[PDB]
């Protein structure tokens, strides 16, 4: 039985939208029909409701690979199998402006720790999202005429260890943004058989945001994410 | 400036009791005189008040190395420099009963990620707490006649990977418990110049409550305010 | 000046279809209009011609990451910037039959050697193909009603070091097939700014082909690849 | 059975002269008595004939470790067990002139890929050629009054990565040349029980022809048929 | 059956004071009652005698992890289970002066050989001394009014590969000194179940001595060490 | 300025015969003309004298890579540039008998510490002896009708971590024996420009001896070694 997410079985939907910040989970729940808080233990708020004719949940995953791994595992134990992460990111290329969106196609990461414990060796396993789901997401964002970019991101483990060199290094490796939990999400999903994808809102540009404008972009895009999730 | 812990100048004390669970931070704040909630952004609760007429703070660090690193870095930017983690752990030896305490003397860990980004290579830097502060914790606990054990712990990055062969491997390596953030706390502290220590409440035994948390929080607070 | 591919400048098209076997390069050239052999040095046959209203080349890359890296680099030096690899692969899942196709979405690999020399450290850089190009490929194969599967593959460096354990290990890591040069192609392309993708013909199933049936599938699919390349 | 080198039973000799370039294999076959093309699949040309009235084969191995591993594995399945690589190399020291030869005594390499799959871990296994065969090569070359050098080489996996700092790093480590397949040849041979050696023609000097290849092929063939 | 230290069982005490220099072993045996030379094979001098109504041995461990690992293993086979390392060290910080002492709380080290062979993987096992025994040492040194510092050290494997960058790197990682065998002593003791500790005499300061001044400090603190060993 | 070997410059010869056991150094000095003890510090005995109208030193290097690295560095500072290791080894193959000799052609080793500190990365540098000098040894042993084998050895860092799996693993990797310092000697000699070689006496056979039989073999081949050193 899950020791972090204390929701009753059946209280978590098969389709889940995961966000790092609890407050955003609460804000996004207002987009659902008849939202109910199904868990608040350890600050990991989970809301379940309806969108279209489908049941869906919005869960908090906290910060970092170890945190999201725990939440995903327990949500799966509760019946979840489809996850779409909706978070913030720091752009690594100058042509992407704050507030715009990034649909992730892959995640780069430094090996070790979590990956070693799960994979049992240092192999560079392809950390990619579900192909179908990611395309559906692209379509959804395209229909709502939202400004987005398709590309790989680097999943950092040390937020406060990202100097200037850091930018040229990862941008030169085909990464257009940095975040912290996509690598874990994709790799764990591939191993567990879960279908996952991710959309990010550019909160800052490292090659060059207000809490209000963030929410404005968040809301405008969450609509595309929910349509996708329930498509 | 801090983008997660949105506290004002002078709202975070120099000495901080850090816990992973927001609920425990709240619960523990009731032991302080006139506790004030100085932050709730992203769910990371931080309280500040007095104990033994001394200013202190109790903060939430979430789960895992990446999370606690960010929290410690921001708390330090707001003025903190002494950290004592008070969490839960899974015993790796059969002779430790639930509800008892473990005063941590070191942390084993798997190389990679966070450590590589901070250390710039894969050397195994000694992950240890402040010598003096740890001895004070030992003193505070024994004075309170509490049942504690002193030993190293393994700081895991994958709670749900910790398999079968797990217990034997880590206990045969000198570790008596498993937790997830002591290695990050100790190493980052040694590197940034912070004084850190850790005491854990045994919540489960892999080889085989609130009363316990409350019972020892006093000893912890006594040490932080000495 | 390239020391392996001795084609004259302008003799290599911007769009290139790369195959491992020289014989297949020769066989596929019959699909082009007015094919001309532009290089035969070191056995790396390169043919250039037209398909639709676009100029396009078919090049031999040999076997392995080190070989394809050299060929791609020299072809790029000669003006190439778009590559689609069309090769054979060993399926890792029982539900994929010989002769069917696999459109690769990512490549897993063991770190070291080539990746270390190019990346300068052990970081697990996302080894993914161009998102747009790969979707175009999917569409092309769909229109011609070809049986294909979308997924990640493992790029092995040791053909004769792939035991039974090997299968369960990589199939459990989200890989549906094993090949030898996709990881190199994708990662080098991401670093150099080239647009690449890959389609494979299942030649064998490790969870369970004649030279004739191979060519039959090859031909039937190369038509979808060329349309994509010149789309 | 071999899926790349499609030769019949008894068409591949026990002793094989291996080269990366198909064109050189063809060229060298003219030095044999009644050479027959026993394979051309995937472009890997293999000839078999006599030299000094002795049966031998000249085979193409392509470029890089992964390619030569496959070729050696299949040649061995067809009966080969003695391999002498004859290729080109880039000198790492300024005192070696183009057209001269290097008899290889060992191969440095970066861990990973191919070696990990075969060795099952990242230990640095000594990558060396057969002691006896290498001394015979030395003897054959000196008898032919040819200018050769004896030393280790670095087997690179990325021809176009070999940067600036490159030359200084590898030459300061005891290597006098750079090539791409000696490490795979030597290690796999030690592991599979094959007798291998390597002689290289200097095609370029990073620190600063067919006549040369032909001139030394004789010494190589003399050694393979002794 | 030990092949390096040819001492007969019963001739090695449960408590052992280990030093790298055979000459220091002889000098220190002078502080014991009725010292007997129990082994001289391969130069590893071992003396056994009494101190404060307790049997104690002083053993030579040579230089480096491989050397000390062998000596500890063999002494343990002969009955030893408590070891206190008394060596010399190079200070990594400016404020520690020559002749002063360092009581070790942990040892950093570069991954590799010895550790990999014993631990069987590259995990960073906490290389720390026995808590009780170490606090005992601290108490003994205070009771003797000796100037000591308490901190971590870096156990180097290459004495002549300790340049300028070196000092800044390791001191910034929380180590106050450099020596060569503590990490091996601590880690092996944790695996084998032995109780170990270490106190070092500062012989040089890499941030900023004669063997005469050394022996004075060595002897000056030798009593504190032996008191701790027999306490 | 050496701090371990206190020999004065001019007292160490350009050619040095190195052994791990101080006792063997003394025994072998018996074969020199007018041997003089040039150093005894830290137990590292060094003798200097003549043999075949040539000055030669016999030096003790202790056990392990760290130990020998220190001794070689210091001897080199005092003028040495040619070293021949004469140690003992455990055979990994059945056909080599106790008392017979092995002339080393290369040394395998586990990555880590010492190598990382000197080389500055984990590259597998070819750890081989000087070609000319090694062929010289082979010739000397043949001229003396001594039974020898020529092959690679594995330089282990943990003597007591050599189990059953161990023997099969290393012998299958082409090594015929195990010892502890050849890889360090060869690699360091390549970096520093010294000319080194090694010949070992089989003292045990891990696949399937008294110090009396040992010394006989040691002395029996000592002349071959010294002849080579002064040839
Ligand atoms: C700024 S709050 C950090 C959180 O948002 C994402 N993030 C946004 N910007 C960045 C950045 N510049 N570096 C790393 N993570 C970032 C991460 O996934 C983490 O959970
Ligand atoms: C039980 S909630 C898990 C949290 O408590 C600690 N913990 C308690 N028991 C364990 C265990 N068995 N394994 C890993 N972490 C544990 C971790 O540091 C994490 O923040
Ligand atoms: C069978 S010929 C090997 C070539 O075809 C691909 N291949 C096909 N089947 C396999 C397999 N089972 N393992 C590895 N590579 C394979 C590789 O990319 C290599 O260039
Ligand atoms: C010049 S063609 C490259 C081929 O010859 C060898 N070679 C020649 N010169 C070099 C060089 N400078 N760097 C790497 N390999 C080289 C390689 O093993 C490869 O098969
Ligand atoms: C100079 S004495 C060398 C011995 O003392 C310790 N030591 C003293 N100073 C240093 C130093 N600067 N670097 C490394 N080890 C040192 C080591 O453990 C070694 O056995
Ligand atoms: C038993 S003598 C140990 C010494 O001789 C060599 N040696 C002899 N036998 C072995 C063995 N079985 N394993 C490792 N080293 C050995 C080592 O280099 C060490 O300095």
Image (cartoon, coloured by chain):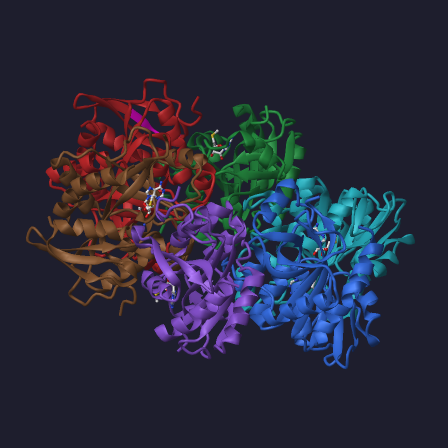
Chain colours: A brown, B purple, C red, D green, E blue, F cyan
Quarter location, residue C41: top left
Asked if residue E181 shows in the view, the reply is yes
Q: Nearer the viewer, residue C52 or E156?
A: E156
Residue F34 point in image, percent of width and height = 93, 53
- Residue C46 lies in the magenta stretch: yes
- Which residue sits at x=16%, y=38%? A141
Q: Is residue A141 left or right of residue E38?
A: left
Q: Nearer the viewer, residue A52 or A24?
A: A24
- Which residue sits at x=31%, y=60%? A70
Q: Which residues are magenta?
A: C43-47
Quarter location, residue D5: top left
Asked if residue C173 shows in the view, the reply is no
Q: Nearer the viewer, residue A123 or E92?
A: E92
Task: In the displayed orientation, state which residue is furthest to the right.
Answer: F34
Residue C49 point in image, percent of width and height = 24, 22
> Measured along the vertical axis of the image, is residue E1 above or below residue D74?
below
- Which residue sits at x=67%, y=34%? D142
Residue A20 point in image, percent of width and height = 28, 50
Q: State which quarter of the image contains the N terminus of chain B.
A: top left
Residue E124 point in image, percent of width and height = 51, 58
Labels in figure, total: 0
Q: Is residue B42 left or right of residue F13?
A: left
- Residue C115 lies in the magenta stretch: no
Q: Is residue E127 left or right of residue D44?
A: right
Task: In the displayed orientation, state which residue is furthest to the left.
Answer: A53
């Amino acid at each position: 039985n899950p020791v972090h997410i204390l929701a009753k079985k059946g209280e978590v939907a098969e389709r889940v939208l995961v966000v790092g910040d609890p407050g955003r989970a609460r804000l996004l729940s207002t987009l659902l029909q008849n939202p109910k808080l199904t868990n608040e233990n350890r600050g990991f708020l989970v809301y379940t409701g309806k969108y279209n004719g489908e049941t869906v949940s919005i869960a908090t995953h906290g910060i970092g690979g170890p945190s999201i791994a725990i939440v995903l595992e327990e949500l799966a134990m509760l019946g979840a199998n489809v996850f779409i992460r909706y978070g913030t990111t720091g752009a690594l290329v100058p042509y992407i402006n704050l507030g715009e969106y990034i649909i992730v196609t892959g995640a780069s990461y430094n090996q070790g720790g979590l990956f070693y414990q799960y994979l049992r060796d240092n192999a560079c396993v392809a950390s990619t999202p579900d192909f179908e789901l990611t395309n559906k997401l692209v379509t959804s964002f395209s229909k709502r005429n939202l400004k987005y970019y398709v590309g790989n991101v680097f999943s950092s483990d040390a937020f406060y260890a990202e100097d200037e060199e850091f930018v040229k290094k990862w941008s030169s490796r085909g990464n257009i943004a940095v975040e912290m939990e996509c690598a874990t999400l994709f790799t764990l999903s591939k191993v567990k058989g879960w279908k996952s994808a991710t959309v990010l809102v550019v909160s800052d540009n490292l090659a060059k945001i207000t809490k209000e404008e963030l929410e404005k972009s968040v809301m405008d895009g969450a609509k595309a994410v929910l349509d996708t999730l329930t498509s």
